[PDB]
Amino acid sequence: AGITGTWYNQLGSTFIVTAGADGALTGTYESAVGNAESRYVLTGRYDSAPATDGSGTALGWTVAWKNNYRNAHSATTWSGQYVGGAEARINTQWLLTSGTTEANAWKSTLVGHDTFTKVKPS
Amino acid sequence: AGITGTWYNQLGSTFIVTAGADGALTGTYESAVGNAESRYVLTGRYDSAPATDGSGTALGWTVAWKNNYRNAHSATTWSGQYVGGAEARINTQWLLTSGTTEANAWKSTLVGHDTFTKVKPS
Amino acid sequence: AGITGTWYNQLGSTFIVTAGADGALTGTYESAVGNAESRYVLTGRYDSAPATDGSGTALGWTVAWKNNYRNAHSATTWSGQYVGGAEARINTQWLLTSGTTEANAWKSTLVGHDTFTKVKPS
Amino acid sequence: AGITGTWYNQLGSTFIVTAGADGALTGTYESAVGNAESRYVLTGRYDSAPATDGSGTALGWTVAWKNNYRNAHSATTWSGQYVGGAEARINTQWLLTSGTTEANAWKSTLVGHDTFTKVKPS
Ligand SMILES: COC(=O)c1cccc(-c2cc3c(=O)[nH]ccc3o2)c1
Ligand SMILES: COC(=O)c1cccc(-c2cc3c(=O)[nH]ccc3o2)c1
Ligand SMILES: COC(=O)c1cccc(-c2cc3c(=O)[nH]ccc3o2)c1
Image (cartoon, rainbow over all chains, first blue to last red; front, side, top):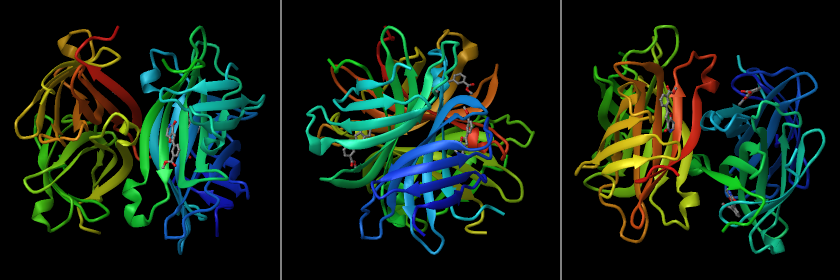
């Protein structure tokens, strides 16, 4: 129900996460897009004692897009909240920074928004 | 990698990180004051095999603003790049999401930027 | 070409825009559908010679949240693209900056996304 | 109000703006060679009656990157605040959306931050 489980964004990427009792997020991410193949390590944190007033649960995680197969020389962070609901979801915005020369730094960082559910889109 | 150690942002904050051999970032984020109550766990990832063309090293990390003392029901992610050389820096953009109700989700996420140096501001 | 007219977001706001031949966007943003004291000037720019390759038409606009009735001492910019066809959309990300003191400048800017359609909901 | 004038960002782009009595911003933005080919129309909005408590003045503007010479099929919005006096600055964050196909929309938008002053960067 909660955060631990297998989630998918609107692009069909797969987010496999475990929420630890200590506030840790660990798991793997597999992207449906970009210069990516197979699973990447993720790590992050979440509020392990959220408000009880109907607010969502704040969280964030990072993937650096290097694994044993490929290296895109970039990293994404997702910042968002888990929303317990009929259909649970994690609503995020993200920042994807590529390593760049200093002259190209102004154009280093993409921004977007991903919504995760436990079902893959159709 | 150049990353392990203590970094300071432009507003006082301090973080101490270990860059592990296969891409992990682990450490703590705190205030200039350095009191324990201001200290929070951080975890993230970085490119452990960056390009050799003078490009920066992509990284990101998360802090959930809960520790043993306090809970802001929110998390920050920093996404950016480490720029080495004579005056090394970590240049970041960040997203701070607070847990909200759905009606308030429009006011859930702050955005900004932080630059970290190895020496304290001023 | 397809932009001019009335758009609805997913949360109860409207706007009416004219896309001029010179790349101008002008109109009115009504934050609460039906409420006249909730109408604000919008101004922006769009690509007046977009590609005809399946790509969206890039655009942006600003609303400063002051009118004759109210003033939130803030302004939103929406940056995005218009997607035509039978189910036309304007997909945006936005930045909402409030005037703050320097001390509070870290908390000045909210980020989010909205999607506008031509049907109120269809 | 303090806003009308010639501003420069940290990259040396030149923002020539007029703040009209009604909340309008109008002018030109150029990236920096002084050349016509590099100059683009901007429009935006600002809070024409800011708070009197020390807070900055909220504002935003858009440039679509089409002129008589070039067309990048993209647009940037800047959202920020003017901070008056000894000396004046406009602090912004920006969103740069390029037209994309639907499949590529996740990579449509860059994010960054620009600070403008009435002097060139040194
Ligand atoms: C510089 O390298 C890239 O641009 C890159 C490489 C591999 C994957 C991705 C990727 C996947 C993904 C996603 O599922 N949601 C949000 C961002 C996002 O980004 C990006
Ligand atoms: C609702 O806010 C909080 O719970 C809280 C508490 C303590 C620190 C912060 C904080 C520090 C910091 C930083 O150095 N750069 C970027 C964002 C950011 O946020 C936020
Ligand atoms: C696709 O992009 C372009 O074709 C293009 C052309 C000329 C200038 C720019 C430009 C200048 C500038 C700046 O000063 N601050 C923030 C963003 C930004 O973008 C972009």
